[PDB]
Image (tube, rainbow, N blue to C red; front, side):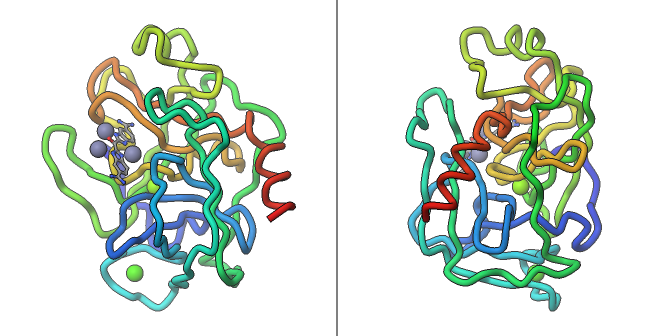
Length: 223
Ligand SMILES: NC(=[NH2+])c1ccc2nc(C(=O)c3nc4ccc(C(N)=[NH2+])cc4[nH]3)[nH]c2c1
Ligand SMILES: [Ca+2]
Ligand SMILES: [Mg+2]
Ligand SMILES: [Zn+2]
Ligand SMILES: [Zn+2]
Ligand SMILES: [Zn+2]
């Protein structure tokens, strides 16, 4: 997250860190046994770490659970990143408490202008590399589809939306991938892609979760 602030320990209790020996992507807890992340974050051997703040220090509120199965969207396209969403089932159910909570799926899609909260342990420099150990947050509005499409001509589909600032400065970035974009208490997006991080007129692009709710509900009920 570039141009954001330290969230505060466990103030984003549905945020998850996907670990394969190190943190490589974020995700969101949607119920005690399931996590939603981005399909471009797919790996074999994922351990889900819940209740995290500093990912390099065990502070006492974490739950480390291995994944039993991963399901990448049937129509995920790795070249265009269309349908960039994946579901991960936990081997054991997580214990929900104040520090570990699930986030709600949307009943409808959010409007341009709506303010959202984006979080993650991804890079914090636009021109440089600095990976934080504690969770970073960023409040950003959903942009209009026309500014999103003018920034990325022929690359935005109906399953994506842009959020951020065209002036540059604040954006999600590599490492934040798969993490949550929560607006009005619902999970509306998944950190997916962008052009570099925080560059002017190159806002972040997110998976539009409201288009996948029936696929999510049907898939977790049958697995
Ligand atoms: N398992 C891997 N090897 C892997 C995992 C995640 C990755 N992510 C990128 C990436 O290249 C990438 N993820 C981004 C997310 C947001 C923005 C943004 N500017 N909003 C830019 C991004 N670039 N490469 C990745 C490689
Ligand atoms: Ca920790
Ligand atoms: Mg994240
Ligand atoms: Zn990369
Ligand atoms: Zn990138
Ligand atoms: Zn990524």
